[PDB]
Image (tube, helix red, strand yellow):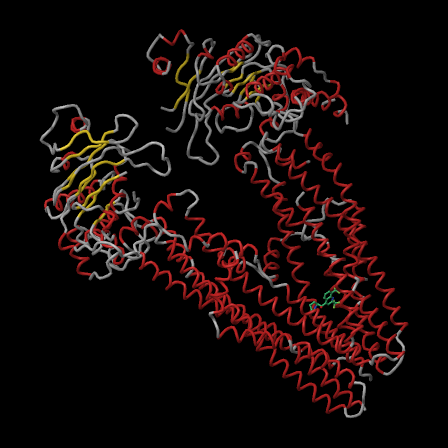
Amino acid sequence: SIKEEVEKELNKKSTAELFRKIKNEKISFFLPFKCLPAQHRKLLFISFVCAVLSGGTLPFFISVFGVILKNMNLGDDINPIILSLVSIGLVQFILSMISSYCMDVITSKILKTLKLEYLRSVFYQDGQFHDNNPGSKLRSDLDFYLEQVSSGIGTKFITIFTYASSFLGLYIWSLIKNARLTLCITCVFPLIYVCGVICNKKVKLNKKTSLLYNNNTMSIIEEALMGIRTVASYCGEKTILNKFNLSETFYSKYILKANFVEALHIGLINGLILVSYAFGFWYGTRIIINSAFNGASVISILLGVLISMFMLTIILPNITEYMKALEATNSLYEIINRKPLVENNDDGETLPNIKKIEFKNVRFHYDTRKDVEIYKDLSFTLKEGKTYAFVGESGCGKSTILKLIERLYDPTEGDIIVNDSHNLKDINLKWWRSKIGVVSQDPLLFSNSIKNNIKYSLYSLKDLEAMENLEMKKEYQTIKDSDVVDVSKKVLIHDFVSSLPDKYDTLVGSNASKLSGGQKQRISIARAIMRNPKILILDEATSSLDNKSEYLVQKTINNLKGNENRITIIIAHRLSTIRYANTIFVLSNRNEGSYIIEQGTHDSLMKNKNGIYHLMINNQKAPNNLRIIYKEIFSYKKDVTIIFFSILVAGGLYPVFALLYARYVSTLFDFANLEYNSNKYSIYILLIAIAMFISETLKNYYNNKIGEKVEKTMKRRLFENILYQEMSFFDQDKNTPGVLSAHINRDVHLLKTGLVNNIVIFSHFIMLFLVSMVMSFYFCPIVAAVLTFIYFINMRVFAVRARLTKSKEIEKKEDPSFLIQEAFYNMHTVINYGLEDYFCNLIEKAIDYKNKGQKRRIIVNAALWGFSQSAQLFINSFAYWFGSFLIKRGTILVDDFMKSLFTFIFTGSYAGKLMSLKGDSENAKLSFEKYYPLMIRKSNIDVRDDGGIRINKNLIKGKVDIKDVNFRYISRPNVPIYKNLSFTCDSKKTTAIVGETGSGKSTFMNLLLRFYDLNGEILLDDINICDYNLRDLRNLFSIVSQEPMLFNMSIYENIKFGREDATLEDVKRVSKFAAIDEFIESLPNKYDTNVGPYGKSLSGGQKQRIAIARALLREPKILLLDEATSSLDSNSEKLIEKTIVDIKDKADKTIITIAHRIASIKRSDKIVVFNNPDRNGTFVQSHGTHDELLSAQDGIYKKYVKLA
Ligand SMILES: O[C@H](c1cc(C(F)(F)F)nc2c(C(F)(F)F)cccc12)[C@@H]1CCCCN1
């Protein structure tokens, strides 16, 4: 979107801001490297030194460059120095390779470790944290941090040192060779950084004010799209567009000012370099002539200084990423360093046996709703060898009971006394959980096999066997299956499993999906049984069973072992499950705390008294698409020629600088008549600078100008088309507001930052390409041919970075992903049993597949990166050798070679610099193809059409006649609504309507304003509605909806909505007649106050009276009311009813109403009611009563006089 882009642009703090931000909080730079062995702590030194060496390369190359040129011009050999490059290049390659390996063996390790540590903390959550940050969010966080640290810690941390070393070569070498020259050169760049700083603020100050005018448009759009119906009826299509257009302009002008300043500064940058070169050569020559020191030594200075100040452009970004990654990890660290509150030691002193588990006034609140206490006087005791039972709903608080028995929530005052001399906190957690069997509402298991799902609890038991006195992987095979076998016959799951083969050898689906729900419950129950359940707890277990499965489970559990000493619980909705019970506790808070209310059994309370249980058992018992765009563009003429000119200049004049540099180099080695040449060339360089500045500036500025004008003219057509569309269009599902605003706010901005930004680049690149390939071959065909062959085959067959990024992205997408996803669903079941079974299993399933792909990826990619760094050296050397080999045998001179070379090189480099500013085009070429039909679609109801009968307000009758209707919504053309409707309203005569609620009453008004065209036969004054030229038809009705809708504009306009030709005095008189101008007169900005969006700064009564006065202004002939006083407070409702009766006293308008206030209905001179006896539709029962037929026959009016 647009807002996100600008927020990203503005919320981009510098390195100084980050430095001051990290200064106070004191993040350790040792933070990412903490879990390292000392092995890696030494290994890291290798890549450190293997970096600094490779960055001490270029100073040598530069200190031999000038001597190559001197040795070449005046006829001598160059062979030794060539070797003194090539060997050096080789060592660079080696070092580069090595460094890669080191990173891709460090990072992964210190990555992987932290993963498990994070994961560990998730399995020591103290219950409440499962509610705080539940599940998937954490995965939406975790992986994010990985991509924020696996892309800011690798090679991009070390390269800077190389560059630093390179800096720390060049300048100081240039400093020892000479002093004054490089100072007089470098004096200028501070004046560049100054301009950059000064221009950034002038960008931002306009950028924000551009946003102050945007969001207003968004509000205008959405606020209008919700209020489509009132806008349609009241004819405010035009006034909105004025607001929209008046808002666009401020935005456009500000953003264009910003773009202008930006292009200006960029041009200045492309200008100053040339003045730098010129003054450099001039001053150097002058001090040579004053000397009587070589000239070649000058050449090696300049480039070096320049390239030095290139490195500062490219160092700084990488740093930020590292720092970014750094703070990211800090977050995760304080997540591992949390302090859960129910953490274990497996060391709490446990007892021999269980007796006297007592409770006293459980007082506990939810963590969020601290001001909502849950239980008040819950107290009881649970002695060994006793059964119990409970009944309730699924939100009363039994979840907290289960969490208390399980030690997940720790109540404040309620005690957990057990055995009368020990606390559950003194007692071990895991010994407590070892002897517990629970089966929740839904069964929850894992996806390996049935027997191993069962043996998980057994593993949890063997843990206690081996811990208090790595055997775990061995003893688990000691556990057998026959227990599961002879208990599987008891739960009657032998036929389903015997049917298909592979009884338990089969692997069951995700969360054991292949079983039925009841069968998964059978297996969960068998698990609970096999784990020595000292207590069995069901949590709405039978809430989703048919009768047979529940009864079989009941027979299974009622006579189950350990009945001498256990606490069996059976919770459910139906009560027959507790037809037998030794004790039943029931509670309620009948609103700040519950407590036990009743006790008893089934028979001794079903027919004993009229308590709660008795009441419950008694009651319940393509081409042209874009050619359109190109047409709209080339209609512009003044701003196409100028971009064309500046393109030609900036393209076909930069290569000239290459040969100009060459012609200076040659004459720099001829001591005679050297001054005149120096002048004659330096001046030309100045002129080139002057031209390039202007050309680039105007290029960028008019580019942005054109894009802006296109967007402005585009949104207008789209919005002005979509506004007038019909209503059934909006009735569709996929015709949503949000999608449409998204189109308007995204696709067009892509259309600017897409097409027009990409076409210019292609034009400029192609121009430079053609001029160079036409220029070089004229001087030296052989060299240019071979060079083009080399770069072609290199970049299109040995494309190193492309293949590298392919490897990175195809690897970044990535079965531990299956297990890790499976875990966070069955969090409950791992808390039931098994914490470190998977802590170690995931490590294995990761490392088994890590290394084999790791070796191939690293051994392939490190060499690619190494060769990527050490190519241009070899190319330049090969070029010089081939050149001299031709020169000495005398086939081509030196100057043609020099010229062709420099042209080719500088143009290639600059085109590489320039291509990295493109934008997205495919998505923009696709969006247009998507939303083009909407800005052309035919509405089928257009007010703009003026072909029909004209009507004048002076001669309106107000008679209506209807015969029959069978209407069917488009949401469901399967069940009709209206059937055989017919009635009348003669003239200035009330007609009150009352029907069954939801009987389609408030759809009839849609038929009148043609919101839904059409079986059905209307007659207004004995002509059908469809030939009245509806432009006028919506200027004499008026509506008072169930809810009004106020717009962000002030009162004076909303009340003037529709009719601008409305003086303030009309507003005053119609307000006093509306009985409203008493609160408004007593406030500043009387007819000027700005309400909020949707009038959220207002009441209901004032809103309604305003909505009514907005209708009264037109003096509409046929008023249409519908239920305007539903649920208002006393005084406003009173004033409103007063105004209604005041209006209805005057029989000057044919009023229609829908109300249920019999005191006002009786005055109605007509009654017509709509019944819906059976679900077929609606039709009339009574007619022509008008209070003369009070209760004479069976109907609904008799009801609405006695019922109502
Ligand atoms: O063309 C220049 C360039 C320089 C140098 C350096 F001077 F460091 F050896 N190496 C470049 C490389 C290289 F592969 F690192 F050699 C590729 C492309 C451009 C390079 C860059 C790219 C934009 C124009 C000025 N800096």
Compare residues 372 and 1017 and report the one nearer the observer: 1017
- In which image quadrant can residue 609 be found? top left
Compare residues 645 and 980 and report the one nearer the observer: 980
Q: Is residue 524 above or below residue 293?
A: above
Question: Across the whole image, how many numbered discs are drawn on residues?
Answer: 0
Residue at 90 percent of width and 77 percent of height: 77
- For the C terminus, the image quarter is top left
- Using residue 600 as the reference point, say whether residue 1024 is left or right of it: left
Residue at 45 percent of width and 13 percent of height: 584
x and y percent of residue 1084 in the render? 25, 59
- Using residue 1041 as the reference point, say whether residue 678 is left or right of it: right
Residue ranking furthest to the left: 1188
Ligand 1 sits in quadrant: bottom right
x and y percent of residue 465 in the render? 71, 20
Q: Is residue 1028 above or below residue 464?
A: below
- In which image quadrant can residue 880 be found? bottom right
- Using residue 727 as the reference point, say whether residue 388 is left or right of it: right
Q: Is residue 527 above or below residue 198?
A: above
- In which image quadrant can residue 1083 be found? bottom left
Residue at 82 percent of width and 80 percent of height: 894
Compare residues 428 and 203 and report the one nearer the observer: 203
x and y percent of residue 255 in the render? 48, 66
Residue at 23 percent of width and 29 percent of height: 1171
x and y percent of residue 178 in the render? 77, 79
